Amino acid sequence: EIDYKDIATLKNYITESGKIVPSRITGTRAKYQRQLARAIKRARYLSLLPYTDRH
Amino acid sequence: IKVRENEPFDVALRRFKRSCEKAGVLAEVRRREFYEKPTTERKRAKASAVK
Amino acid sequence: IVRGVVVAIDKDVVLVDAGLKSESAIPAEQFKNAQGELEIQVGDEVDVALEKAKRHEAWITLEKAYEDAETVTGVINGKVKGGFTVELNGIRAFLPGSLVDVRPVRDTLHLEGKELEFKVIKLDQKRNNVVVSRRAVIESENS
Amino acid sequence: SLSTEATAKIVSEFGRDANDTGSTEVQVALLTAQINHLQGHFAEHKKDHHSRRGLLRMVSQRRKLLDYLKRKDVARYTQLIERLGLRR
Amino acid sequence: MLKAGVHFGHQTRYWNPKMKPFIFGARNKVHIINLEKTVPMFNEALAELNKIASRKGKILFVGTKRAASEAVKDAALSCDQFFVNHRWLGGMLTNWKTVRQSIKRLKDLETQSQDGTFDKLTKKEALMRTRELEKLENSLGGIKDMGGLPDALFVIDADHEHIAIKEANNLGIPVFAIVDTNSDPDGVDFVIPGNDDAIRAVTLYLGAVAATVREGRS
Amino acid sequence: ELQEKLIAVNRVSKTVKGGRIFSFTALTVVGDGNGRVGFGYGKAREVPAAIQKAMEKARRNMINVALNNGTLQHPVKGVHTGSRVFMQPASEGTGIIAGGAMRAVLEVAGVHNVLAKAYGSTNPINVVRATIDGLENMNSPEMVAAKRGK
Amino acid sequence: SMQDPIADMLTRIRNGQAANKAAVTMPSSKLKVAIANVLKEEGFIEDFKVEGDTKPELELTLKYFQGKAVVESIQRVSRPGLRIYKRKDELPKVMAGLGIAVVSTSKGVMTDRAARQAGLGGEIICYVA
RNA sequence: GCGGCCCCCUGGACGAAGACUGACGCUCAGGUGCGAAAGCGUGGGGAGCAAACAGGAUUAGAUACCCUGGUAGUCCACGCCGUAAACGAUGUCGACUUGGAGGUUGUGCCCUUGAGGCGUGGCUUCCGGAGCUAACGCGUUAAGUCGACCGCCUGGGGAGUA
RNA sequence: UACGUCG
């Protein structure tokens, strides 16, 4: 949430095809949905997570 | 995106694509860049979602 | 938990007095025995802890099932230190990581978000819990 | 805006003491410091029309305070604009 | 006369700001009526209500919700008084004229029913007519022997029976209501901050009212 | 001692399936001649039924006015829908000198000699409604002295 | 910004009468206490009370005769945009005498009756009807 | 008007406690600045899309809708233009006047005995009370009750034209 | 056309 290197946590908050899950599904108050998404994107730049599942 | 299965399998049963891509996401990107119709389509979509 | 008295009993509906702004109404499904009848009458002081609540006193009908290894369905929702809490019929289950986490060969992320069918062998009505078996792993993993 | 050390230095120079941080000379000098610093910023960029709106608020507010202090004590006015090198 | 025993107020939801003088209002999201305010209010209602009850007046209890029935039939009928316990017809006070001829049909059909020609000429139409006596009997039940429009009105819920309050205010009839924290003191002349939907509370409550209606100097 | 008089009859229409259907509306004001003014609208299919419904509604729904000797007390402004209306007591300012549809309500009201001038709209159905509102919120020196102590 | 505190006071009293308010607080001044003393004297308010030390607060206990409110219509006449200074002959009566008009005369803040009796006109502050 | 992520330079807002100045305020004609899109100038760029244009259809006709192509343009730098249903068709600033359900962002207190309970601010959405309104509706973010200053209106067309 | 009422 605040951190992007913890990709266990980030990998919970992402779907099976690399897409960020909405806060309508996972709860996650909007502040942490914003930190979350921004951390997911920083992780996708570092190739810690994938952008998609067809690379 | 992928599916596989071991030898107990009969039917496709891939409703992973009624989850993400097929129905909405590709039919949406067939037609025009507006900025304008989406602001009102989303306005009346969120104004229709009411009790 | 609330202690109340039965005052009005109109078929399919039972009226219990508690002492709030309204008197609760309990469906006969909670007061019915295994024979197919009732076990109460007007003037009886029964117990009622509040159909998303009648299950707390409806699990008593699942005993004759867990006596012969009754196969049910559940889903993991909680996780702590080696302990997993599964929602089985609304009862927290216990699953140690003896086999859940050991000698990682690959990306073992098929745990948080799994919805399969588990088997039960022993039940504890003294700790209001239901510990899952261990050998049943040959069914939950790859059914 | 401005550095904490810079603001503290200007409050120490222009106030009666520190904690006298709302006096008219002090506010004028802090606005002046920021106006000059952003002269350096807007010599470059030049199409930061949003930040410039903040800058023109600083210019206008400095002007209001100089008009106040001019029609309250003119000796403080002349010493002030003498020291800050404004008025041209 | 006895202190309100068991109701202490209700209605977390849809509470009405005009009930703000009557609310103590603490526990678990629900509002508690200040019963130290209710007791003088309810004693006043017994005062003026006994005052018109001693002038030989008609009172008309109103009890549409459940279980105000048959508690309003029991309390009104324990006195020599009148009641509405099923759906209160829109306009049985303000056009009582037309409701007078419906009451007249109820009298003529019960006189025709238990004494006169009930088995006469048809079975099907006789069944039709008897269930007309069930419909006219449960709708125009208590009011069938009134013969006037009444001198007071005692309603058991102010928001659920707003129609009857609106008509008795339209006609200049004193309205005596047990309001709850959702209700509104519209034109209720003698408001009583209480609990509208507890059967203990309305049987205690109507017990006191029916006690003072027939109270006798003897 | 009832003193009824009609102000306006009109023919309104409805436009059903087969052609139009024409109905008539009356607008009358009754009053005893000493306060006690009412107006009634009433509408029906013929003119005498319309005026009779209008009188019958106007005999009830009758309002008290706190007159002076034979007239108003202080200048009063009553408004209704689009119709703004001034009145001035005109302490024996002889004769009722009001507009149409205001002369009638002031005539049967029992007032004799006021000065009026309706402004705004001067639809007769709303210029009374702006005379009663008006004469209703006009209060007397024994009412103002009742309010404020003395 | 606040540029007419008197009209603000009269606004507080109109909207307090209109909301069945028991009492009305506001910031206080010499002119508001003068007007409030005229209103209590003429019977349009029940009482006033000025409290506070460094920030005074005028409080007007309002009147309600029946269910209706006593102050029927209070208007500000001499607003800051356009000030109105009447002589002792031009000095108006409101509701044909049934309703005072608070005029600030040189002798003090008076009513229309009191200042027409005192023989001196001034600045007409407000109509209370 | 602004939508990947990162850095640099930078504007504003809001909150908590305390300190300081001490009416320094509000509005604003002329004036100045900013101002979507299309358009214009000079120099780049040009994948997609696409006025113009061309072909195919449709049609009575089809200078259109539909199809296949497709140039300016859209993109960048600097300058111009100076407008829009530039719209909450609602000028700015301030004060007062019943409520309910949310959203978003602060902060204080209490067993934090959890995804709590009690308050206190900032911005915002929906519904509604009095009141107002021609009605429709607005409704503490007013179109309610007031004050200050500005802008504008005066039948339709001709004409926002000469 | 067209809406104006009694012993």
Image: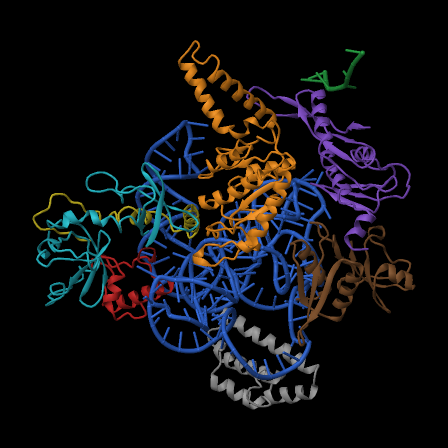
Chain colours: A red, B yellow, C cyan, E orange, F purple, G brown, H blue, I green
User: Relative to H56, does residue D69 appear above or below in the rendering?
Assistant: below
Q: Quadrant of residue A15?
A: bottom left
Q: Is residue E139 left or right of residue G126?
A: left
Depth check: give the residue in front, C60 or E71.
E71
Depth check: give the residue in front, E198 or B23.
E198
User: Relative to E88, does residue G87 appear above or below in the rendering?
Assistant: below
Q: Quadrant of residue C91?
A: bottom left
Q: Quadrant of residue D86?
A: bottom right
Residue E209 location in percent, x, y?
55, 42
Residue F66 location in percent, x, y?
81, 42
| Residue at x-position 27% and y-position 58% | A19
Q: Quadrant of the C terminus of chain E?
A: top right
Depth check: give the residue in front, H67 or E159.
E159
User: Relative to H22, does residue E89 appear above or below in the rendering?
Assistant: above
Residue at the limit of the structure toward the top, as seen here: E121
Residue F35 location in percent, x, y?
80, 37
